[PDB]
Image (spheres, grey):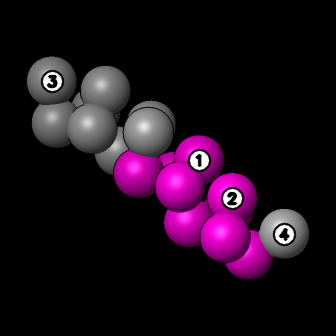
């Protein structure tokens, strides 16, 4: 579940970025 966690966490950082 930590991975489902790194997934949304990756789209969040990339969301702010661009």
Q: Which residue is mark 3?
A: 1
Q: Residue furthest right?
A: 18
Asked if the stretch drawn in magenta spans residue 11, the answer is yes
Which mark is drawn over residue 15?
2
Label 3 or label 2, whichever comes before in sequence order: 3
Q: Are marks 2 and 4 in contact (CB under 8 Å)?
A: yes
Mark 1 → mark 2, Cα distance in angstroms: 6 Å
Q: Quadrant of the N terminus?
A: top left
Q: Quadrant of the C terminus?
A: bottom right
Label 1 or label 3, whichever comes before in sequence order: 3
Residue 6: image location, x then y, percent: 35, 45
Q: What kind of secondary structure does the magenta stretch mostly adopt?
A: helix
Which residues fall within the magenta stretch? 9-17
Q: Is residue 1 left or right of residue 17?
A: left
Instruction: Give the structural element (helix, strand or loop) at label 1.
Output: helix
Mark 1 → mark 3, Cα distance in angstroms: 16 Å
Above or below for 17 versus 11: below
Q: Which residue is mark 4?
A: 18
- How many other residues sit within 10 Å of disc 2, few (<14), some (14-19) or many (≥20)? few
Label 4 or label 1, whichever comes before in sequence order: 1
Mark 2 → mark 4, Cα distance in angstroms: 6 Å
Mark 3 → mark 2, Cα distance in angstroms: 21 Å
Please tell me whether mark 3 or mark 2 is closer to you in this view: 2
Q: Which residue is mark 1?
A: 11
């Amino acid at each position: 579940d930590w991975l489902k966690a790194f997934y949304d966490k990756v789209a969040e950082k990339l969301k702010e970025a661009f």
